[PDB]
Length: 458
DNA sequence: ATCGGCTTCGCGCA
DNA sequence: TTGCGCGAAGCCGA
Ligand SMILES: Cc1cc2c(cc1C)N(C[C@H](O)[C@H](O)[C@H](O)COP(=O)(O)OP(=O)(O)OC[C@H]1O[C@@H](n3cnc4c(N)ncnc43)[C@H](O)[C@@H]1O)c1[nH]c(=O)[nH]c(=O)c1N2
Image 1 (spheres, rainbow, N blue to C red):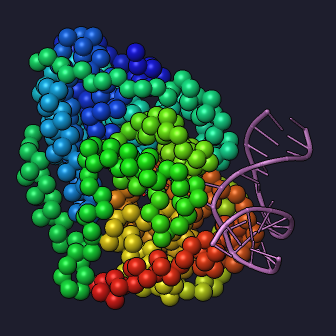
Image 2 (image 1 turned 45 degrees about the vertical axis):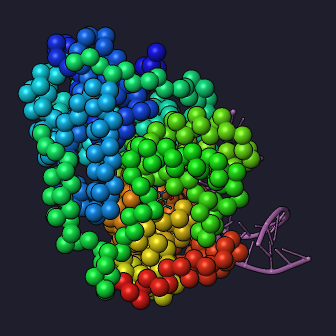
Image 3 (image 1 turned 60 degrees about the vertical axis):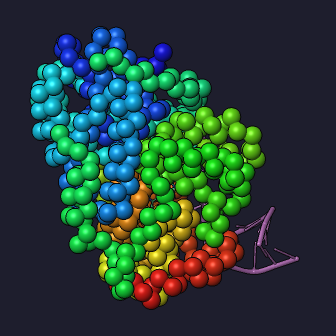
């Protein structure tokens, strides 16, 4: 019943007579998960129960309370949802390449399954796991509508090369999800969420008046809330998306990106629901292009350039152009600290930084601006990269994500873009100006909203 | 082929 | 505001 182009064999072996174990990692939800649906099947095709394992890692120390609380409040709800269908969830603390490896032994796992990520480190882990299990090891793309290694086989130069590949594959791969069959047969998150927050408090972004910057109430975490954010977008916001998606003063975005990043909702379900929805076709076309083409070319990009977060993976015309302007006199140079605390000369730029700092989700359009100004106002393209990756990943609820590196790459280095008119400092890299912003939206509204923060933020 | 078209440009202009 | 034509620009893919 499940399309088998979704499964890839990591380590062929003989099946053990124990349970099927889903090493969960990317797709932290219970519904609409091909990898957990696939685990139920081969557990049922062998009469063993299915179980799920998650592994907390030391990565959360590289970002903030905001995301750790987002993720873990998701797991507390997941965990209950899984128990309801009799599927135990066990949570591990440490390096997967050792902990998953042990778990597979201590539990006599018959077969191992994991969801798919393109980030370098998940493959580092897969290979320590492969190297230490005797059972078989299976990988299922639960994140993409069309499995990343099937849509294309090379790096897609631009979205217009990639778009027909994927759409010709859609009619075979866009299906409804079966329901999750309950089966028949470590630590507690409570303490895990407390130790982490006690460890992350020293970094928690505060204002001069001691209070935190972050506003936790713009995005309730979990599978439930995410489903409600999709249903709402589809009824109130999808008709307006094409027209109003570049207005930072509206709130016409879907606001799914923090759910999708953590897999708290399946992008395949959004597609299904949008397709079936009767709205302005131009909005459905413009929205599907984001959640389909751009989301998955971002996976295609990471999976095929391991240097995804470095200057080297820029296309050639862009490396040479930026090189030629390495010795240009930047108008302004800021340090990482100065960007962070919104101390530029450009009250629009600082505004988008206040929106990132306090909410954890910067508007789609401003994110572009945000990034191209860092290039202009740093001493080199490598610092621009570094500052951009650092701030994005540390402050976006949807950061540490393929969409993130591929998005910066587009802004700073023209991955998936094209060559525009040569400029000093920024080369042939597409330019964006404050007056360019002015004909698109009421700049001073934006500026006005977050003006009150910068005075207070230290 | 080899020429047309390319996410989300800026800017004059009506 | 908002829609259009133009400008500078490298490259894939039918
Ligand atoms: C400098 C910079 C940095 C980043 C990003 C872009 C830029 C220019 N992006 C991509 C994009 O800015 C971001 O995904 C949206 O703001 C997500 O918000 P909504 O769900 O509200 O988008 P919206 O409703 O407009 O679109 C819905 C979905 O489309 C996808 N999408 C939209 N724009 C995209 C883009 N340009 N590239 C890839 N996928 C895109 C996302 O999956 C998003 O969930 C990204 N994305 C992300 O999830 N995490 C990140 O940390 C970053 N980092």
